[PDB]
């Protein structure tokens, strides 16, 4: 309403919002596409892969 | 005696003392009676070949409840109307009561603010280069500590909100809501009859007596089964899968497993009821072992404080803190969504870094506002052994 | 399973690491990575009685991820770091390809013996074995918790 | 909202008083020839199917 | 769920159910209202004609 200047580093143009990046979401799926116990029924072994996991 | 145990020529003697000696002449490294037995060469430095930094990001399982505010104001409020059954009209009464007033009565439960949570961390550029035999692994160290500083947000938020509805499932809702089971081979029939109670018009299954303006009265309501969830131990979901759906024949529309939020154990959390002060130094170290750096001696815990890890084994903390868990682990709390009011405000999540060059270590901060609450004006049934 | 995929400060042994005696560390798993380990009796009982004599199996069959053995022990550890004394001990040991261990060296306390060995007079008390103590056993884990590197160049 | 609850309450009132008078009838009317006696909870599964 | 041959026998097209079959009460030994607390309890359900 009041026009003013609206400008400071913080508390101007930093008081009402900021840049948003990430809301700490479920991307790793818990209880949708993992937390699974619904697997197949047949011949069996070796769905067991290994990455390097060095980073 | 041994040159390895001699700490006074290590790389920590030059960073606590302001003055140190500039050049060096080396050493005559040995492998005689160390942790570095070597058959062929007693005079070489132990070569390591790699390090790994294993790290997995962790979820929240509640991000479809993530409604977003704009962070203005601090009180919210909601209210229903009490139900009011009609009467038989008896004409022996006076002809003047139609002038008399009759206001409708309301519920009026009021909610305060949430809590803003925060965490900080410090990356050094000086001593960290003495480890990290390449340069990329230090960058992996940076992105790994950043990803754990966002994953812990998830695990603490799900743990605290799990704690809040389990804490609600004790000592808050009345005896017309709770029912008494006896076994895990019970409580599956009892949850199966407990569901499709709620699609009968009833006032026995809410808790509006715990509202402010509605202690006496009643309030009928229902639910819609795209809207209920059940909350239980993974043991019970294990029982439902291996026994109830497995050992029977035609359940082609009956298997209600899509509403089963289930956990390994329904408690790791602690709540202070008696107030006190902090005196033990190892208690301070144990708190900042989990990151609570702000705590000093002489500090004062409030009443409405949770603790989210096992903290009940300190001498300040015995007796006055309490674990929130079911007793006999035969536990099933069914509710309906629109009752739990989850909220967070996190657009200002990553604050700009502070550099501090004269110590040369950057420091970040993470802030987010979060508002847990649940609403009493819906349908809830708890199943336990008292 | 369904506990292995919860955010748990337990289920790991970070308290038995080097720098992590105090504190917590949460981890989950992915169902492409859980390995069951048990006897053949348990797996056999499963796939002839439970999943056979039940009706619905439509998603439940976790037998894809089970490894089993006829027994979980034929193997031995050392205690007390004993010494070689007897002729019959070493020449019994000769029968399994061992040649270098002559009468007069010691055995370190962390060695393994990999066959039925405890009946020698030097070994009783000094040598213990590795088995489940009750033959009713299932150790299940997240895979790539085990690491296994060999050099066969 | 107060108006639509002033019709919702007469709805729930009407239905539960009507099931109440049905139970009242079941206890106080229909002399012994009309009532059959089950024993167990699976007993009446057979009884209603034959009835 | 268990008796395996339902295509024909499913009589759950005609089953009215309820949580309880009674929360509704009945009066014997007629009386008079004589406590203020009792009528204040009745005011919390809409009954305003009571004295």
Image (cartoon, coloured by chain):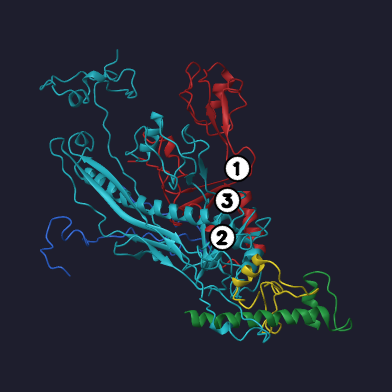
Chain colours: A blue, B cyan, C red, D green, E yellow
Q: Position of residue C31 (x, y in %)?
A: 46, 57
SS at circle 1: loop
SS at circle 2: strand
Query: In this view of the protein, can residue B247 be seen by the observer?
Result: no
Labels 1 and 2 positioned on one and the same chain: no
Q: Nearer the viewer, residue B247 or B202?
A: B202
Q: Position of residue B87 (x, y in %)?
A: 64, 81
Label 3 – label 2 distance at C-alpha? 11 Å
SS at circle 3: loop
Count of marks placed on residues: 3
Label 3 – label 1 distance at C-alpha? 39 Å
Q: Residues within 10 Å of mark 3 (few under 14, many from 20)?
A: some
Above or below: residue B86 compared with residue C3: below
Q: Residues within 10 Å of mark 1 (few under 14, many from 20)?
A: few
Label 1 – label 2 distance at C-alpha? 43 Å
Q: Residues within 10 Å of mark 2 (few under 14, many from 20)?
A: many
**Quadrant in the rendering for residue D41:** bottom right
Query: Along the horizontal axis of the image, is B30 left or right of B204?
Result: left
**Quadrant in the rendering for residue A13:** bottom left
| Disc 2 target residue | B333
Name the residue located 29 percent from the left edge and 62 percent from the top edge.
B72
Tell me whether circle 3 and circle 2 mark residues in contact (CB < 8 Å).
no
Q: Chain of mark 2?
A: B
Q: Chain of mark 1?
A: C
Name the residue located 33 percent from the left edge and 58 percent from the top edge.
A24
Q: Nearer the viewer, mark 3 or mark 1?
A: 3
| Disc 1 target residue | C71
Labels 3 and 1 positioned on one and the same chain: no
| Disc 3 target residue | B326
Label 3 vs 2, first from the N-terminus: 3
Labels 3 and 2 positioned on one and the same chain: yes
């Amino acid at each position: 309403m009041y026009e003013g200047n609206n400008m400071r580093s913080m508390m101007g143009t930093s008081y009402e919002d900021s840049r948003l990046n990430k809301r700490t979401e479920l991307n790793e799926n818990m209880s949708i596409d993992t937390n699974k116990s619904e697997d197949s029924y047949g011949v069996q072994i070796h769905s067991l892969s290994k990455q390097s996991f060095t980073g | 005696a041994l040159l390895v145990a001699k700490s006074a020529k290590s790389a920590l003697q030059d960073f606590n003392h302001d003055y140190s000696k500039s050049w060096t002449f080396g050493d005559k490294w040995d492998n005689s009676n160390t942790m570095f037995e070597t058959f062929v060469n007693k005079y070489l430095f132990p070569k390591i070949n790699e390090t790994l930094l294993i790290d997995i990001a962790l979820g929240n399982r509640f991000n479809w409840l993530a409604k977003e505010q704009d962070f203005i104001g601090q009180y919210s409020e909601e209210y229903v109307i009490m139900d009011t059954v009609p009467i038989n009209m008896d004409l022996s009464k006076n002809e003047e009561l139609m002038l008399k007033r009759n206001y409708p009565r309301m519920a009026t439960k009021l909610y305060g603010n949430g809590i803003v949570k925060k965490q900080k961390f410090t990356l050094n550029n000086n001593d960290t280069r003495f480890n990290f035999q390449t340069l990329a692994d230090a960058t992996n160290y940076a992105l790994g500590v950043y990803k754990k500083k966002i994953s812990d947000i998830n695990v603490l938020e799900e743990k605290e909100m799990r704690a809040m509805l389990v804490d609600y499932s004790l000592n808050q809702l009345s005896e017309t809501n709770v029912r008494k089971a006896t076994s895990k081979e019970d409580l599956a029939s009892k949850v199966f009859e407990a569901i499709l109670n709620l699609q009968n018009n009833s006032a026995k299954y809410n808790e509006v007596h715990r509202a402010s303006g509605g202690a006496i009265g009643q309030y009928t309501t229902v639910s819609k089964l795209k809207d209920i969830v059940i909350l239980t131990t993974d043991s019970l979901k294990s029982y439902l899968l291996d026994t109830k759906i497995a050992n029977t024949f035609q359940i082609a529309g009956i298997d209600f497993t899509d509403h089963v939020i289930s956990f390994d154990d329904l408690g790791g959390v602690f709540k202070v009821t008696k107030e006190f002060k902090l005196q033990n130094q190892d208690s301070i170290d144990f708190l900042r072992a989990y990151g609570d750096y702000q705590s000093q001696l002489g500090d004062t815990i409030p009443v409405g404080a949770v603790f989210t890890y096992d903290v009940s084994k300190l001498k300040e903390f015995t007796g006055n803190v309490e674990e929130i868990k079911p007793k006999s682990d035969l536990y099933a709390f069914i509710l309906d969504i629109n009752s739990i009011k989850y909220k967070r405000y996190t657009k200002g999540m990553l604050k700009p870094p502070f550099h501090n060059p004269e110590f040369d270590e950057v420091t970040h901060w993470i802030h987010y506002y979060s508002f847990k609450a649940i609403s009493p004006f819906f349908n809830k049934i708890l199943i336990t052994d008292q």
